[PDB]
Amino acid sequence: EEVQEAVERAEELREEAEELIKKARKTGDPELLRKALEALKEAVRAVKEAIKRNPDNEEAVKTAVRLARELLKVAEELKERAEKTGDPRLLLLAAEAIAWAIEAVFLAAKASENTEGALEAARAAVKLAEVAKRIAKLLQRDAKKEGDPELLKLALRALELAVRAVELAIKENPDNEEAVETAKRLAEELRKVAELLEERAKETGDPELQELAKRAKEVADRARELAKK
Amino acid sequence: QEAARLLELAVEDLKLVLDALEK
C-alpha cells in the first residue's frame, strides 16, 4: 500500500520530467533540464522509500530502472549543451544526473539480487568520482580566472557528490583500493578548495564563504575515513 | 539490467567531454 503509493508518485515525476527534456531539446532552458533533474531526484527518493520495507517488488525495480534511463537523458543533453556553451556548471549538473542514475541502478540491482550489475554500478561510481574531481579542478580554474565566488561553491558541490559516489562503492566493497585511493584524492582536493574558500573569505568576510570553508574540511574528513578504512 | 553497461558509457562519455573542454 505505502510502497504502491511511493512507486506511483515516482512514476508521476518521471513522465513529468520526460516532457521537460523534450521541451529542453527544442533549444530549451538549462533550467528545464534542472527541473527535470530535481523531479527525477525526488522520484529516486520515492522508489528508495518503496524498495525499503518491500524489496523484490518488480514494479519498484522496473520503476528504478526507468528512472536511471530518464536520468541519463538529462545527463545526455546536459553534456551536449555543456560542450556547446563550455560551461563547467552544466558538467556539474550532468554529473549529478549520473550520480542519481548510479543510485537508481544500484538500488534495483541490489534489490533484484543482481550482484553482476550491483558491482558494475559501484565501479562506475568510482569512475564518476574521478570525473567530479576533474570537474572540480576545472571550476577552481574558472573561479580564479574569471573571478566568481559561485564557482567555488560549485567546486565543493562537485567534490561532495564525488565523496557520495565513493561512499557507495566502499559500502559495497570496502577493499577496493581504486575507490580507496580516489577517496584519498578527493580528501586532498577538498582541502585545496577549503584553502581557497577561507582565503577569499578573509578578504570579503561573508558567512557563506566561512561556512562552506568549514564544510569542505568536514567532507574531507568523511572522505579520509573512507580512504583509511 | 543492461543499464549497468549503459551507465559506464555515460561516465566515460563525460570523461571525453570534460577532456574536450581544453579546446
Image (cartoon, rainbow, N blue to C red):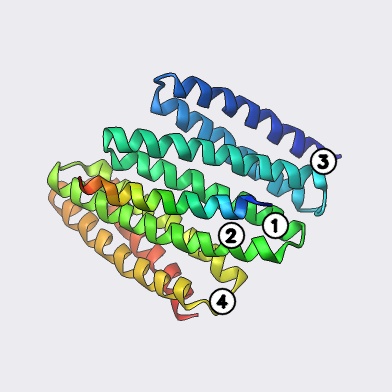
Q: Secondary structure at mark 4?
A: loop
Badge 3 and badge 2 in a common chain: yes
Read off the residue under disc 3. A2
Q: Separation of disc 1 and disc 4 at Cα?
A: 18 Å
Question: Closer to the N terminus: mark 2 or mark 4?
Answer: 2
Please tell me in which quadrant of the rendered image residue A77 appears.
top left
Q: Separation of disc 1 and disc 2 at Cα?
A: 8 Å
Question: Closer to the N terminus: mark 1 or mark 4?
Answer: 1
Read off the residue under disc 2. A121
* In the displayed structure image, the side of residue A201 where residue A67 appears, left or right: right
- The chain holding disc 1 is A
Q: What is the three-letter code of the residue carrying label 3?
A: Glu
- The chain holding disc 3 is A
Q: Separation of disc 3 and disc 4 at Cα?
A: 33 Å
Give the number of the mark in front: 2 or 4. 2
Nearer-the-camera pick, A28 or A136: A28
Residue in the image at 69% along x and 36% along y? A10
Mark identifier at residue A109: 1
Name the spot of residue A208 as percent of width and height, x first. 30, 46
- The chain holding disc 4 is A
Question: Closer to the N terminus: mark 1 or mark 2?
Answer: 1
Residue in the image at 65% along x and 60% along y? A117
Q: Residues within 10 Å of mark 1 (few under 14, many from 20)?
A: many
Please tell me in which quadrant of the rendered image residue A91 appears.
top left
Q: What is the three-letter code of the residue carrying label 4?
A: Pro
